[PDB]
Image 1 (tube, helix red, strand yellow):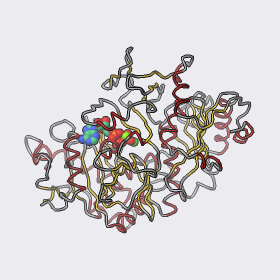
Image 2: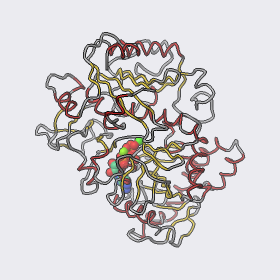
Image 3: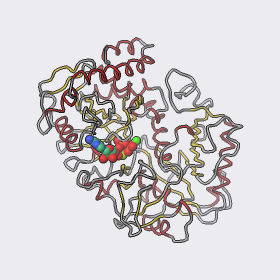
Image 4: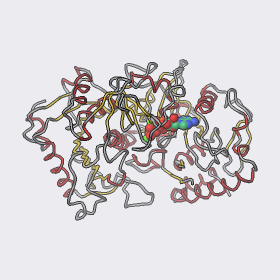
Amino acid sequence: LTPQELEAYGISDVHDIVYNPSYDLLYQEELDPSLTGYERGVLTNLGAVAVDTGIFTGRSPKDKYIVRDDTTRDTFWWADKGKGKNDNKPLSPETWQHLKGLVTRQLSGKRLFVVDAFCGANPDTRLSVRFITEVAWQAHFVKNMFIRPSDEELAGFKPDFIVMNGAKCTNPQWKEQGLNSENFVAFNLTERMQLIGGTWYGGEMKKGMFSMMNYLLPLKGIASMHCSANVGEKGDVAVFFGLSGTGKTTLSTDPKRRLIGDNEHGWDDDGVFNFEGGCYAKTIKLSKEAEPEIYNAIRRDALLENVTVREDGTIDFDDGSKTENTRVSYPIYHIDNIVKPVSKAGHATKVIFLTADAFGVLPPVSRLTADQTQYHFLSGFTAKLEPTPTFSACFGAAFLSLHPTQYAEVLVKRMQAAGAQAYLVNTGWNGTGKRISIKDTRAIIDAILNGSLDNAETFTLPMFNLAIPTELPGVDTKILDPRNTYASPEQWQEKAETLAKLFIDNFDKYTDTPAGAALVAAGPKL
Ligand SMILES: Nc1ncnc2c1ncn2[C@@H]1O[C@H](COP(=O)(O)OP(=O)(O)OP(=O)(O)O)[C@@H](O)[C@H]1O
Ligand SMILES: [Ca+2]
Ligand SMILES: [Mg+2]
């Protein structure tokens, strides 16, 4: 609020502070025709502002660093201490101070936007975050994606985390400091700050705080989950884990169910709760007949990123020539059917693992055993494209601050206490070399949530030993068995053996505990 207050963080000579801009103020700030470069917004015919995020159109895990100090040394899952790969690269406190002078100097003597907000729907576990930026649309991003405080909550607002966005500065000493590049996304848990240099991508702030929630919550016994969530009229809660592009936002935004959130949730003694106040949807080749809710949320106060807007202001949603990662964020009340005023609900009884399998091996749906649930949670499989595999522990290893086993343990405890069941859903590819359609996927989710799948007759799919139904109301029976989508079942066999090998090698790192070694029997077997 006052310059004396920003000076505590290291920023000086700030004349104009814009505290908690309203949506109307951000709209005017973004459309100021005097803006230059990547600060500029343009109005689209849908009424929503669109921006260009610059060189970076996604996260930069190679530039992510965590200060290694006595607070984090023995608790963090470090990239250099084994046994599993992750992006939590250690940083010295000395280099941290250098990066902090870079960002604070860049922000000094600027018009700064400051946004106070919450991460976490429950007062007992939420972080009070203070975001500092010089770009209006960046402030708009965090206004959309975090929980917007009431007037009364601003009154006594006490930040316990600061994120300073120094996107316009770069680090010229990076080669001497052993870093990946002149950009940086740095975290210091002793100071409780995130610094961002060089990249304008707003997702770094969203996932920065998620990584911070992923550090603190499981240490209190609370699951911290990379998943969307919604609840039926009968009060039944479902969560949908998955890696990028697998359908968390697409498939949780069903107007029969009340949306809880689309990306980040905790699970405590009272149930599943959203960390966020908005949604962040992929728009590449957006249909509108396939995703009407998401489409109609694109209006004033939504923020489009990197989409092509024509001279007449209309949007070419099919154009990925800047990036396939085109995006729109919006506050969650742009969705008509949501839980409100607080984004939370009871304990989940359906746990869905979304995966997009470019190898075309995995069945569209399968009810997992309790051990297959752990095996597939720790594996975190998806594949892209020709197919390249990704194994990302807990379906979100980019954001884990603790060891994967820690997340697995908390999830199992919550699931067992609630009597929850888990399901593996391939929203990716089959023998057709096409992605299964959203229509067919939505019907499969319906069969999961309404008990149809639990009461179906099943057989065991070989190799992966996954229980699959012979038929389901609403679904093409042909696709339920992935072997039928090839001309010869021997074609599937060949790819299943390839994929099973990748799973087996990947899981080996978990077999150094007796419990992990016993899970190998739940995995695929050659
Ligand atoms: N059968 C399907 N089920 C779900 N999504 C599908 C399907 N086929 C294609 N898609 C596309 O996949 C994308 C899913 O985007 P979505 O925002 O749901 O990703 P996400 O899982 O939330 O990941 P991110 O965290 O990157 O946003 C959309 O572009 C959607 O249209
Ligand atoms: Ca994601
Ligand atoms: Mg999404």
